[PDB]
Structures are given as structure tokens and as C-alpha cells.
Amino acid sequence: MPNFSHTCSSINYDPDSTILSAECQARDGEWLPTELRLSDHIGNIDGELQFGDQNFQETCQDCRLEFGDGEQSVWLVCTCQTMDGEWKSTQILLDSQIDNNDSQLEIG
Image 1: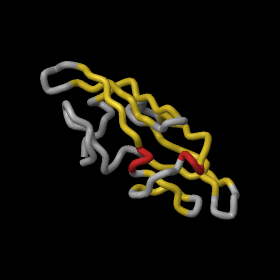
Image 2: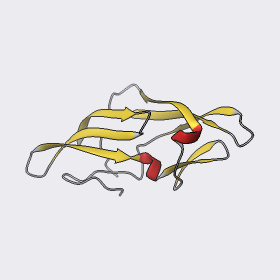
Image 3: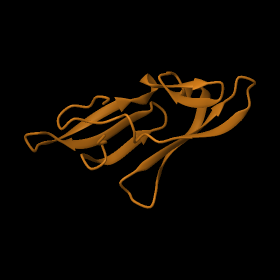
Image 4: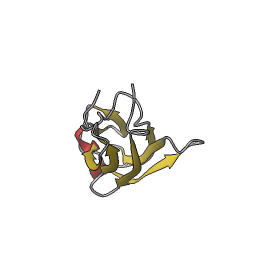
């Protein structure tokens, strides 16, 4: 269902504190800024990235968003260390079971 793309603009993601910042329009038509911490639903699992877990940037580096053919989407890729200590590249699409209300930001 709907995502924070068209509803919000100026998608920012700091790789240190992993916080997503973007301006969204409220029901009153007013524009406000919102922040979100993915670490809450993203953790490391034997070298892979999955939803439901937490604490991932601590064991991962080079996190960066990537725009596809249409700037209406950005994709999250990060290198996460494995339990043996090896480094591997994983990928994950934020667009999915996540959405933002007109004036509030909460999972759908």
C-alpha cells in the first residue's frame, strides 16, 4: 500500500545514526519534517538483512540509497559482517509493508 514517496519529498538517510528524514504534507495542507529510525525494525542475521530484527549498522558499513529509472524510489544496500567476520553485500527495498499517514508516520 502507498509509501512516503509521493506523500513526502527530499528523502535523506544519514549512514551513521540511520535516521530517515523527509518533508510530508499534512491533512491541513501544511508541510512538516519527520524523522524515523530503521534500526528499530532492521538487525543483522548471520550476514543477511531482514525486517523484525534490530542493531545492524553496528555490524555493517557503506550503507547507501540508490535511485532507479524513476526518482520515485530509492534502494537500500549495505555490507554486513558475517559471524565468522567476513564482509558480504546484501540488498533490501524499503518500499513494501511501510507507509506514512498524511500527518503521521507509522508502519501499515
